[PDB]
Length: 517
Image (tube, rainbow, N blue to C red; front, top):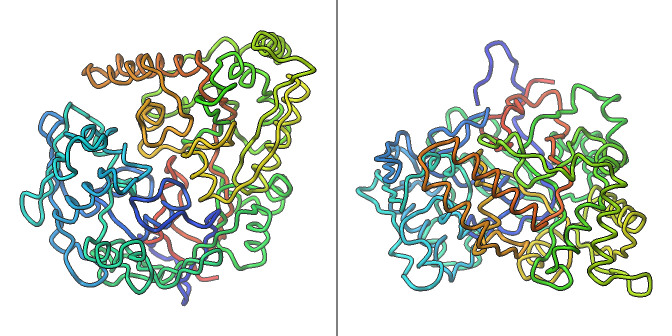
């Protein structure tokens, strides 16, 4: 943390943050969500980290170079250490990235190594080559070298993500699945795990072995698993919570802006809210069905009437403000809703749906006041505008993610936030073989367009290919884009260090501080 000259620090430097749900895991290779990553950034530190404004900055690596954007060499700081006092080395990273790549780890982010194009990743993921064949090596204890199969100019930007953070081999091997328990875990971020009560709280305490520990101000941070945005706001206003999760209650949001304007933080956020269609399950394997749902959804109603929190109606997967996005707004988005509805009704009728045999399916969402209210509204909009019947089903976060990976669903509420600020952070998740492809979308044409982006050595050609890839996704109606999120949350006046300038919202508690109040 960088405490401005003249600010008075509170005697007690403790923080309570709501985290939206119970985490899937504390193991960096078994996680894929925002709640998981929120805790991960405090416990595990990779090569690079985001600074307070989100710029890729030195993490375990103090400096790095690239040779033709294909061979990246990371110089690790000599004083990087784990919470048990042992050094963080290049060998930790070799082991960790191999474990991420190994099919037996079954990481939801195994494909992150394909996104960066680390040498031999496809064969390793497919079980054709051993994980030890991955294009990574420790040149010495403090030098980690990464070899890519093609030039990736933005490669370093990927390295702040939890999936590429180091894990302690000794603990993993000795304790297996219980390595993340407080008594067994070993961490290298600014914090260490003190307590973990499932569905109650996660308590982290400062890690004195952290290389930058002298600049850490908060001594303890608690992460709560409250999925009710109303409850989160209530416990924030009661004094228990210092920072809410960034999902706001429809019930209370308007009032909050007028009641505590200075505490309501609303900043740009590179995330897209959409309805994920299971593309491999009939009748959703029919583009006419998918297009009808996409068109019959009234974004103006949802975004400006039901939600009204500053979100922008979406027509794409990648947010248009992503660095490098030069997207073409589709013609259907410019139409009137009635015109969209007619087209939707016509396509559904074409697909074989009548009043006698209407389209009926499930709408899965993770337990939440916001998602339930949006799902009820969408169910109503689709019933009125298209004559479809929707069965709402809620599931806890971890279960919900597993269900989408399993393909045991029809339509699911979804949200994707950038891992790095570049269009492929979104587009790569729709590749036929992506470990993050929960839409179960497989398009050779889409795959080709993205493959071509690293075959050109020009940003204008790359951007045009990204625009074409979005048009392909849109023509196939892979998903139902709803809106581009805004990062809205409540932050107590005494919480210093949260600028809200980072569009990826990669917060580190080590950068925050409590002002005397």
